[PDB]
Image (cartoon, rainbow, N blue to C red; front, side, top):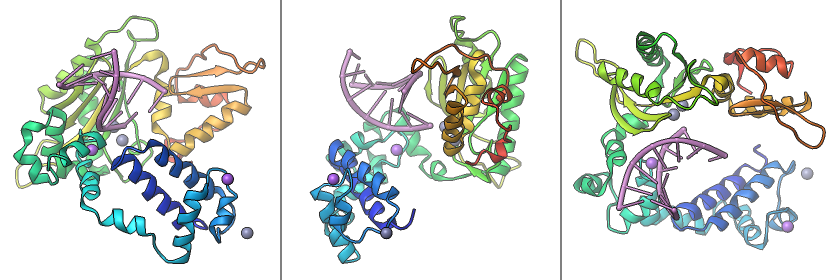
Length: 327
DNA sequence: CATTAGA
DNA sequence: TCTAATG
Ligand code: NA
Ligand code: NA
Ligand SMILES: [Zn+2]
Ligand SMILES: [Zn+2]
Ligand SMILES: [Zn+2]
């Protein structure tokens, strides 16, 4: 957790590099498992050879460990850290819609900077356009103060459109959190579930609503169940306009909302942990359901859920406020 | 680990 | 269709 801190970090730097700059999925997959096990190793790694004993570490990584142990740095690391091409990719990549692939491609054509990007907006698609356009606000955190305002607005329209609608803003915001990255709104309706063959309009109506009043300004991606966009709080009585924020609305079959809602609220650890418990307690929990465990090794048959309560009950736990779903 | 774009 | 990107 810190005893092997640096080694795991150099290692991540490394893996991360293979993956983006070059396309060395293995090297890259290599670095990660190593960074996984040494992280676990309950002792201070004093030399490669020692590390070496590990499963995952080979002669390769051993080597790097030595040098780093030896001298407070890594050359390969110093070099990559320096090199502009690699720098550039790690940068373009920051743009919503720009991934490693397009990053390497733009680089190879010479688009290295954000300006370069502008001059060549034609080379960009719609997602990437929006990304470029809101680059700044996109890197910005969301004050909870703003979060509640937002939430307020979405909830009301959703309601006004159809009172049957059910929405939950999940995420950290849900878990109390002082700030959040983007707004995730979990959505489901009663006429929509597991079987009842869709009702795309069900998503589509609200999206339309939200745009109608300018809450939604842009559209990154709109499908029959997932809409990815950009929204914005009405810039008051001027002097101050609100930064553009990422927003995702998603359709859920009412018969699997809570699993979903439960799920998405996290924390990543609360999950796994909740997840690990359901196993002893003879179950299975995943993104959409909770199934009883069968001795034959496995089993199925989807437990009927009406709230986050039922789930706990099932695995017979204490209902944990989302506030305290921290781990 | 799954949904939407794209070309 | 595959492949990218975001989640
Ligand atoms: Na080994
Ligand atoms: Na990006
Ligand atoms: Zn020891
Ligand atoms: Zn989020
Ligand atoms: Zn999101």
